[PDB]
Every structure is written in structure tokens, then in C-alpha cells.
Length: 478
Ligand SMILES: Cc1ccc(-n2nccn2)c(C(=O)N2CCN(c3nc4cc(Cl)ccc4o3)CC[C@H]2C)c1
Image 1 (cartoon, rainbow, N blue to C red):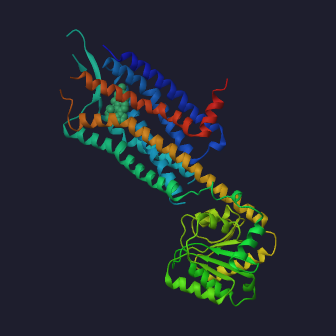
Image 2 (tube, rainbow, N blue to C red):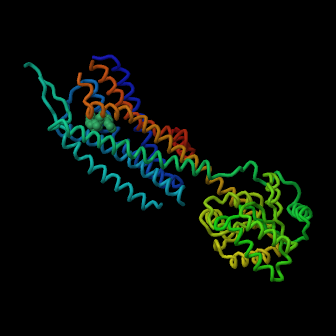
Image 3 (tube, rainbow, N blue to C red):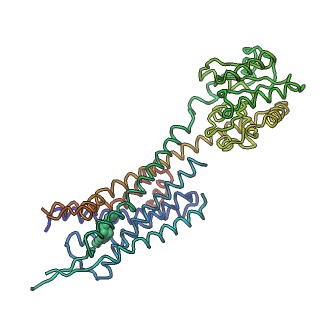
């Protein structure tokens, strides 16, 4: 014995050094730089600690056993080292699960460091408890006389128990949390990439020409309106969704007031023929109200956002205030409902918030926007622009971290698939009961791969995380 031995020793050494240095540097990076202190990164630290554990205590023993096919260490270590192995695996899996859970909770339904600490502690306790059977079953057996060798292996009192235990181990440490994390991360993907975001390259002021005053003058001239504060609605005509009913009702409330003559309204969209007719009746009734049911290009809408004073977003429900972001990027000030999404983007410095379906509150907000429009609104518009850009920035960042995490999950799944399938085939379906060197080679490789995962994570952080890469950079600077 044996071929593939030098590549096994070499690979184990490489993995050992890279995993040790790498995960230690991960922990150092998070601990010494405060901007690194996020829930995700605390969890990541936990992961690296588990990896360091299994790297120090299990990897060498595994190399020796896979090389010699014997157990030189004691009975105690024959209990301990497999126990530490399984515990490390459990900690890793549950840590990934808590990461995915955290991201899902923060992204799909918009988590403190204390909560995260509790999560960590729980993870380690659960992991240590559920892996007690592993420690119980492991036994040393003497095989033969001139010599004798001892091997360390699971001792079962039947054929059913190992099958059940390894089914359970496969489900708990691999299959179920993997499935759950996949579901969570695909929902997260759909949320962050497909439903969130904004064409920042299109929705910016650079494409418009002339001052805002000139554009507004052109706007009102084109619409056949006198000068005055201009409000804009763009959503669909629904009852209980985009809230054009709230706006129409509030317009009726305002129409009796003397301030109404100072206001201008641009209501755009299709939908309920009753609401469309209501809009058209209000349009025919008042000269300072214009209704557009026809389809408008993005360029025209962009010009609108860059010309009007305020944009009214009276939604009952708005998970993604993309209209708000588009308008704010072009200097339009939002008067929106305090529903989650608009509630997220807009603050009291970057717009006006109102109760979702209260026409009185909306009319009051419109009046307030008028009195506010009696003076310079520059600072306000700039605040809106910078808030929108900041929000978009945050979305892109969340995309980066989420992609990194997904990649880690994938690499984990890949790294643990072979040993999983092998264990299930051997222990549950009783295969490999008959050419042994091939099976043994597959097993040695699978073991090495499992340990290779631990070295895989930190370099993943290096290539897919700017902050981690920068701290790694600072570390290796001699
Ligand atoms: C070496 C190694 C690495 C990873 C493994 N893995 N499978 C699934 C997840 N991870 C296994 C493995 O097949 N396990 C883990 C616990 N077991 C185990 N035997 C070990 C022997 C040595 Cl020298 C060191 C650690 C040992 O862990 C026996 C039961 C069995 C289920 C073994």
C-alpha cells in the first residue's frame, strides 16, 4: 500500500493549512474590524470555528486511518473524534440554516446580535446533544496468531438500528435543511433580483435638460394648465390596492377649498371603468385636473417625474415602492401611504407619509405640500435623490451578500453529497457487501472532500466579499 497515497497526504496537508489559516483569518477579520459586525458575519464566524475544530481534531486522525486502515488511538478517542466530527457537521448545517433564515426574514419580510448569540448557543447545544448516539455506538474491535490490529467502527446490535440511524443522520445533517435553505434562497432570489431593484442607469436627472422650473413650465404649457404646484398619480385604477379612489375622494374634499385653485393634478392609468369614469367626471368638472388613460413611454414618464412637484402614492398595499424610487431619483417629492415598502424608503426628510386609506389625511398632506411649495424645495428634492440612490445601493449590496451565501450553500451541498450517498448505500441498503479497493478509494476521496469544504469557505469569502478580501489583504501584508 498504496497508490494515490502521496496525493492524499499532499491534499490533506494543503486542506489543513488553508483551512486553519483561512478560518482563523475569518474570525480575526470579523473580531478586529467593527464594520464587519453583522448577524451574517457572526454566524460566519461560528461556521469558521466549527471548521477549525474539525480541522484540528479530526482531519489528521482521518488521514492516518484512511492510510493505514487501523486505529492507533485509544477507545476514548474512538468515541470522541467521530463525535466531534458529527457535532462539527451539525453546527455547520444549522449555522447555514440560521443564516438563510435570517436573510429570509430580513429580505422577504422586513434580527439583533443578541438574537444571533442565542441562535449560536442553541445551535451548539442541540448539536452536542443529538450527536450523543454517535459517541455511544463507536467501539474498538480487535482483529486477528502473531499479530492483531484494532479498528474503530460503529457497533450495532442488529441490522435495523444502523439503517434507521443513518437515514436519520442523512435527513437531519443534509437533506431537510438543504431543502429548506434552497426554498428560502430561491424565494430570496425572486425577491431581491426579480421584484426589487430599479434601472438606475435610466432613472437619473442627467438625461433631462434645463432647470426644473423650465421643465415644469413646459409641462404645464403642454397640458394646458396655469402655473401652480403640480401633483401626479401614475398607478393602476384599483379599489384597495393603488388607492386612486383615495386620491379622487380627497380631490373632491379639496375642491371646495380656496387652495384647490392653486393645485394641479395629473392622474394617469387604466383599470376600473367606474373609477375611470369618476376620474373623467372630475376632469370635466375642474380645469386643474387632467386624466391620462393612454399608454406612456418610459421616457415621457421620466420627463413627468422630473417636471412635477409631488408624486402621490396612496397605495393600500405596496411591497415595492419602485414608483417612489423612480420619482425620487428625478427629484419628485413623494406623498405616500405609510405601508411597508413606501414606509421603508420614505422618511420625514424625504417625503410625506399618510394613513393608507384616509382621504382626509391625504387631502391634509396635499395642503401641507402646497404650503411647503410656497418656498424653496431644493434641499427636499436633493434629499429624495440621495435617499433613493442609497436605497438602491443597499439592494445591490444585499444581492452581493446573498449570492455569496448561496455559493457557500452550493459548495457545501456538493462537498457533502458523495459521503452522504456512500453512507446511505452502505449503511441503509447494505451495498459494498462484496472489489473493495475502489469503494475504499471513493470513501477516502469523500472524506478528503468533506474536509476540503472547510478550506473552501474562506476563499469564497475572499472572491465574493469585498470587505473580507480587504481584511485578508491587510492580514498578509508583511
Ligand atoms: C471521516 C468522516 C468525515 C465525514 C463523515 N461524514 N459523513 C457525513 C457527514 N460527515 C464521516 C462519516 O462517514 N461519518 C461521520 C461520523 N463517523 C466518523 N468516523 C470517523 C472516523 C475518523 Cl478517523 C474521523 C471521523 C469520523 O467520523 C462515522 C459515522 C459516519 C456517518 C466520516
